[PDB]
Image (cartoon, rainbow, N blue to C red):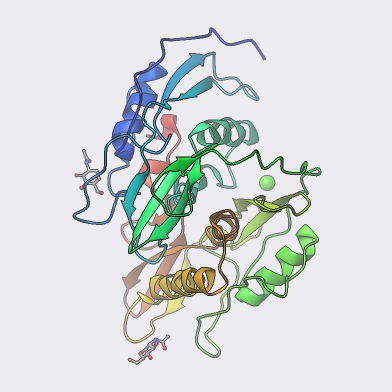
Length: 347
Ligand SMILES: *[C@@H]1O[C@H](CO)[C@@H](O)[C@H](O)[C@H]1NC(C)=O
Ligand SMILES: *[C@@H]1O[C@H](CO)[C@@H](O)[C@H](O)[C@H]1NC(C)=O
Ligand SMILES: [Ca+2]
């Protein structure tokens, strides 16, 4: 590939809300901010965004080259603004609790489509990973958060810099798995097998919150997905397994890209969301029962974010469903990419 044209000017120290930070990042690369991220990962209704805090604010700069096959067009650099060092105080998120470290998976999954080119996926991954990583603890019904090399002290009153965790090196990534499908226990078993890991006796495992014998149709809705594993040895402060996902479509199995048709439950198509809420409520409660430190909670939660997340339209007597980053089209006949996930040229 050709080398980048290098650097446009550094931004000011950047901050939230997400739409505003995305706008400044996009302008920094010399591009219009065409996505509307409002409502995708905002704070719960009624909560003001606090001022720059936690070593979480940062400057950004960008460089550009032509978008060629195999040559991602953009390249970024991040410099943390450590002047804004007071600990962040944030509300608990519905179902996720102090989930600020892994909510970004919703946006990363925009580039997990079967038709996302590998070089595109890797280019956006580099961007996402450069954002300062959040480390949160819960104190008296609120979240106390610091980013990057800083973590909350035990009392959640200050951001401190622990000794470097010096995590062991990852081994080679696996290949993609085959397309995985429900029931959930089969998905879980396949992850253990594909990633060559164990159910730690103290560990967490999601259990089906589905009724006794609900009908599971053939793979559909871009809901079936492949996984790719990167694994490192255990070490305190270091979660050992990182998972990537890639949805399956019509070139992966013949029904995989067709909309899902399900029966209604209790006269509605809400049951997928209800089940998702239950799984997260149970995980969040388990993370506290088992006294999980933030790095371990976050590691499990990032994997749990990879489960299929459905949106359904009720059409006649049936539910027509697709999984993120897809949603049903207007008449419930096909699956389409959510607008804020579309590639820039598809917008
Ligand atoms: C952006 O999305 C939010 C929520 O979906 C909506 O309330 C808002 O009006 C949208 N803005 C534009 C300019 O489309
Ligand atoms: C259906 O309704 C019953 C009682 O109203 C409730 O217990 C159940 O969780 C609902 N959904 C399913 C899938 O059973
Ligand atoms: Ca393929």
